[PDB]
Length: 464
Ligand code: HEM
Ligand SMILES: CCCCc1nc(Cl)c(CO)n1Cc1ccc(-c2ccccc2-c2nn[nH]n2)cc1
Ligand SMILES: CCCCc1nc(Cl)c(CO)n1Cc1ccc(-c2ccccc2-c2nn[nH]n2)cc1
Ligand SMILES: [K+]
Image (cartoon, rainbow, N blue to C red; front, side, top):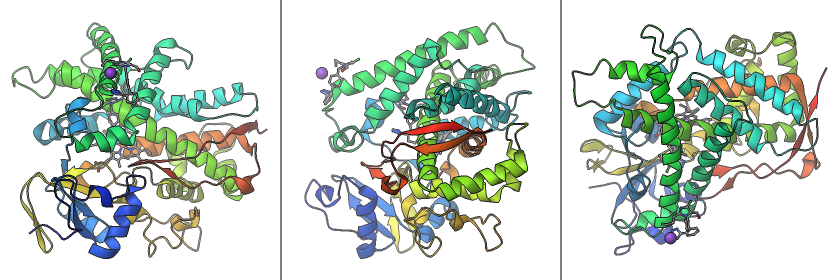
């Protein structure tokens, strides 16, 4: 038998007993009744939900391979998304994940480190902030250009200028699809309809923008096919073509131009929004808690100084700053239910049997907001990541990137973008709120499977 759960109604399952507004709250509520493991029916489709650290750890880590599948919904087909990493499964996934992990190492693509690409961008990020001349500002756009430009660098061997139109178009389309995909209507409600697509227009728009991006990725690929030093692959494309020119006798292969571009779109998709929002939300949290902003800056002044830009080495000699970044990610809880998983085979899990294919909903919130581990888990406090001596305190419950075999491919790159961009900003700027901190409110605004910070403006005031 499958786990227990609230008895569904005929043909709509448990649809109307789940608050579509704040799903994570609804799942947590259900846990208080049915426990750490439970089933919901999303219209005859069962969904096992894991909730709390113990359940999540033993599914995702202890039974990693079994829980390594990606849950597929109709939106996967309508927006054609199962051909890269994020939404692929089986071999296709195993191979492309692995290649991408290797390639995304810090020195996986030649002499230029990932870290050097990020530092170059942190520089430019700082420079744009200057161009705002200390006037009010909605950092949404600027802060999103950086993580996007890092992906551009990783994929095409170098960055764009923030006013280059090719870049602006790329970003526009990315930003459009992300906002579209964030609608409850597309993420949830259209998924109730397994065959008929009630938003054909929207999917058409989504695909039209993917194609624009794909077509650009092809213009670059071709160019890389005539700048090809086989001994110095300078970016993700070179590395991919290399792997292609080495599987020529293993047709058919997972590595083709089709998969390269699908994978590149996955990187753009996964790489810019969440990093971008996390930065935006970090600023808002620093504005609200200026004692924190000040202590990070003490660390920056003492360890880094002004004669140079920050590097990843500094991180180990900057426990307060490390705690702050960690606390931002834990508090904001951006993907409260990760990405749905699926089991790969028939699996006994605790008391119950879960059939192969069954969708699995991991509650990251449950872990990140565990109160034994993080007392007062609803209130931003770097102290959650600090021992009584002021050293950094690791946590098994730090899973903003999820856990196990499907853990964020970008874990390290994100942490590098979070640590470098924030230290770089706080190194050269002080932050002023337009309105008084007292009435700012940084509570997450939550809409389906997405947390987001509330609109705010601020001034980037230069120091020294
Ligand atoms: C603050 C930043 C980020 C957060 C919080 C985050 C979080 C996540 C989460 C929760 C997942 C779902 C994992 C799962 O299915 O269990 C995921 C998947 C993924 N992330 Fe990120 N991520 C971030 C940044 C990035 C960046 C910069 C990249 C750049 C390469 C990236 C690439 C991916 C990829 C490729 C996947 C799909 C992994 C797979 O299914 O095999 N992420 N991320
Ligand atoms: C299939 C032929 C048209 C496709 C399409 N490509 C683009 Cl570009 C546009 C921009 O609005 N569009 C049209 C489009 C029209 C309606 C929506 C939409 C907006 C809000 C609420 C429902 C809809 C909708 N989606 N599908 N049908 N109606 C989205 C995109
Ligand atoms: C111009 C192209 C814009 C990017 C975008 N539009 C479309 Cl449609 C795809 C579908 O794969 N993509 C790529 C896409 C890939 C993965 C995700 C995903 C990755 C990690 C965490 C959440 C996201 C998510 N899924 N749905 N919305 N955002 C987002 C976008
Ligand atoms: K239409």
